[PDB]
Amino acid sequence: MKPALVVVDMVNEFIHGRLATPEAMKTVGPARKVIETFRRSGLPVVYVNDSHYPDDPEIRIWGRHSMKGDDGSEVIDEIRPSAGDYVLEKHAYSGFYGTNLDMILRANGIDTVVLIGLDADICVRHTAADALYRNYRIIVVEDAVAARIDPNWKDYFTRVYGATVKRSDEIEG
Amino acid sequence: MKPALVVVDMVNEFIHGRLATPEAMKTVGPARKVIETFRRSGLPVVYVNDSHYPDDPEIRIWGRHSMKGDDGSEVIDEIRPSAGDYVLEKHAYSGFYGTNLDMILRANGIDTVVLIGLDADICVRHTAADALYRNYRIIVVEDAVAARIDPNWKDYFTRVYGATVKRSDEIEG
Amino acid sequence: MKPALVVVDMVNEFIHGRLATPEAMKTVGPARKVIETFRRSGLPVVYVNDSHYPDDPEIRIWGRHSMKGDDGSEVIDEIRPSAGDYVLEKHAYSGFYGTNLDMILRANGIDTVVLIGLDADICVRHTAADALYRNYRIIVVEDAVAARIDPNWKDYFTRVYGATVKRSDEIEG
Amino acid sequence: MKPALVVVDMVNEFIHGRLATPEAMKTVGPARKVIETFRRSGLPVVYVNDSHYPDDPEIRIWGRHSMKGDDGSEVIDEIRPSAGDYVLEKHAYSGFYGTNLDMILRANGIDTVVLIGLDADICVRHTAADALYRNYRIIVVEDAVAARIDPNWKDYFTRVYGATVKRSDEIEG
Ligand SMILES: [Zn+2]
Ligand SMILES: [Zn+2]
Ligand SMILES: [Zn+2]
Ligand SMILES: [Zn+2]
């Protein structure tokens, strides 16, 4: 296995600001733990963050959120990115759509994505879908992901994306 | 509005054959009804059908199904395509991934996709996501789509893709 | 016609710095003129600039150039982007690959791309190619584009991408 | 190295039929030679053939050619595909655009594409670009490719895509 960690939407507006929830806050400790081990082990860490324009397709659905330029779209300080970490702006749910995520994964010979962040129903899941199409294996760190609407999310990942589910305190590296 | 109809995985495998959902049969009369009205009105009809190779990414998850060359991957006779419905082979959940769906829709000036077929909560849903990404409006025909795992699938479409839900017996054309 | 202006790689390293040429310098006046008219007319202006990582595929070919973070990848001051202009980072020759260029064009209902910048042999041409695949019409402003290796570039655009060639002092708006 | 052979537009239209280059005939013996060695060695062989609709973007440029359903879009008998060579229909210059080429290459763990067919300076070249974007190494077989407009095509491949150029009678397998 050669994995990269993809950290989805761990940004101020969903953790600290206007759309903050406790489910979201609960992810921060575990996320820092997962991020830290990947770094200490030299493997790629990639942040993929909403950085929306007013006319992005999904703005009609949600209204303005995690806008480009506004501090809402910035990664929370708790897991501030370091030198060597990749930071990507995205305009749709999936971390792959309109981004160079796939490039970075291919350039570092990656065959497995480890997914954490916000959230199990929308962006994490959508990123997972695209990973599958592109023949990556998928791992999700349950305690580092927050649900929104679906309580059967874990089941969906496993049954539909063949994902294996782990906890932050586990590490196959 | 200028819509195209995208007919997802109405193949023998998902209807009559092996992986068929129980309510999957019930979509066939509504699907024929929707397809017919689109045809009678000159608008594009596109069939997107799993046509798998043994090493497609999702084979490890589901095992062999709707394989290229085998009759399981063939559109059911009830709604046999005419010339010139478009018939596309796909290798992943989304009707857009690795296909020329978007080309067809762009070439015919389309701004709205009308979605029917199987599964409501998998291929139809993954087709909807990629439609949203590409700035198409989305319509799902509730009685021409079959769910598999999620019973809250209608809610997901509307809340996550801003889709509007219609019945086969309705027509805004 | 509803056009957007795509301004390719008008960045310091190719105009002012390490890979500066007079062909390149010659584009600046005309580019400012084209950019200005688009702005004065409310139509979208999109800068697409190399912002490379060390391991981008093309770095093996060219060595480091227009690197992310370094002033070489910054747009020249002469045509500094304004409020409302879009500024995109790209990692390959085409302005579309791994970017949200197509999103912006679709969100603003665009059907024609007007191409200027660096250069007619590589990035402008590659961007043109992708525009074609995505069913845009193509216009190139000859005096606002610099050749590198091919002297028959104008012929290639017209014969292969069906591009129409204009001069900066002309305007169909 | 783990290579796949991509065989571009060796169809009746480009060889025997209407738009055929004069030296296009001369590629057929080398192409068969390259194809045969790949087969004898178990490596993937993928045919990518124009299979146009009347409203594909390039029809306005070239007029009708290599149309879907017409024998002009059929692979020449000299190098008839076997089972299981992959045979892909494409609608644009690049063998990647709107196709599942990348899926096949990824599923077979490929890191290098070997390119033959027509035209050296159009479809073969546009296939090379998209290969570079996707971090594949590139090999062109000079005698199994035919130029159309540009006589400096070999130089373009090497200088712009870092391609290495080989003859059909050579084999690094
Ligand atoms: Zn968002
Ligand atoms: Zn399937
Ligand atoms: Zn570059
Ligand atoms: Zn063609």
Image (spheres, coloured by chain):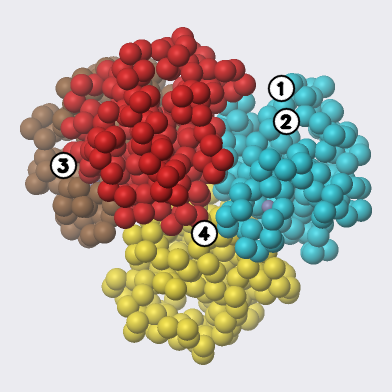
Chain colours: A cyan, B yellow, C red, D brown
The residue sitting at the top extreme is C18
Q: In this view, does A124 lie to the left or right of C17?
A: right
Cα–Cα span, label 2 and label 4: 30 Å
Image disc number at residue B135: 4
For the residue carrying disc 3, how many other residues have a C-alpha within 10 Å: few (<14), some (14-19), or many (20+)? many
Marks 2 & 4 on one chain: no
| Protein chain holding label 4 | B
- Quadrant of res A62: bottom right
Q: Nearer the viewer, mark 1 or mark 2?
A: 1
Task: Return the x and y of residue B57 as percentages of the image width and height.
Answer: 57, 48
Q: In this view, does D48 lie to the left or right of B35?
A: left
Element carrying mark 2: strand
Element carrying mark 1: loop
Q: How many labels does the image show?
A: 4
Q: Is residue D65 above or below residue D144?
A: below
- The first of marks 1 and 2 along the sequence is 2
Q: Which of marks 3 and 4 is in front?
A: 4
Marks 1 & 4 on one chain: no
Q: In which quarter of the image is the N terminus of chain C?
A: bottom left
Q: Nearer the viewer, mark 2 or mark 3?
A: 2
Q: In this view, does B159 lie above or below A14?
A: below
For the residue carrying disc 4, how many other residues have a C-alpha within 10 Å: few (<14), some (14-19), or many (20+)? some
Cα–Cα span, label 1 and label 2: 8 Å
> Do the residues under discs 1 and 2 have CB atoms within 8 angstroms?
yes
> Do the residues under discs 1 and 4 have CB atoms within 8 angstroms?
no
| Protein chain holding label 3 | D
